[PDB]
Image (cartoon, rainbow over all chains, first blue to last red):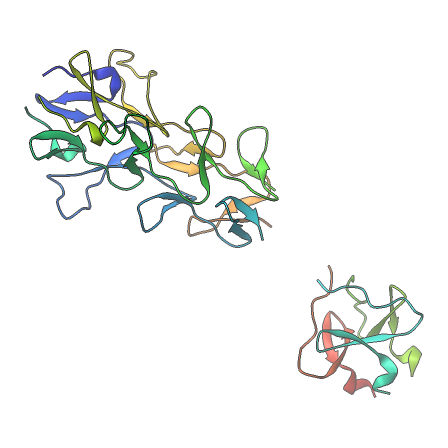
Length: 100
Length: 98
Length: 102
């Protein structure tokens, strides 16, 4: 058999093998391993698989996906300046004299 | 024909095939599909392709690439053992109001 | 010999070749290239390889990996007082009950 070795194939003791380079590996953890190992991507920090085996970015605190699957990002306000003093109650600035 | 099955190839009946696992798939969306499908990476949220067919991180609102291809982006009351309230953008001792 | 052409293989002048599409390429920069090229992923902005060839996200200013490999936001003003129906005043960086002081 002729193989095109410039297109990712090579011989390993006369058997055609995928010659897997950067970002790829053979999955030695399937039910059929180590005799039958599928090729898979090789991934590290910040990448995962979803349920379909698709690569996704691994998002932590502060980050989310928008509506197109793009990565996106995602202290109390000032009381009124009317000369009057304010205290804090149930998430609101409430006039001091309310309690005096 | 001899294939090395522990290196990503398998027989699909009599025919030699790539055995694609996680992060990989066959592209059924070409002109030539379904009879000739290239192997491609399998991608989801957070990843996209370039025009050059390269995988890139898919960035939305608030994130961008820096110039070397990496992803990038009331004051406290006085501390003096006394109680304080908010008035005109200042922190003003409570006592002052009693 | 027969190949499953719907499974990522094709003929190039009789020779069996991987038919590489989006996110893959052959590496022409090896010690046996260009007559022998491995298949590799094809990566651009936001991605790199680690030392062992695994793809990682490339992080710049203000972003960091946490200890579980996830991308996160890297790293005074007052917080909310208690939401318990009571009034509060600020003393020594703590919300203390206005009650105390009357």
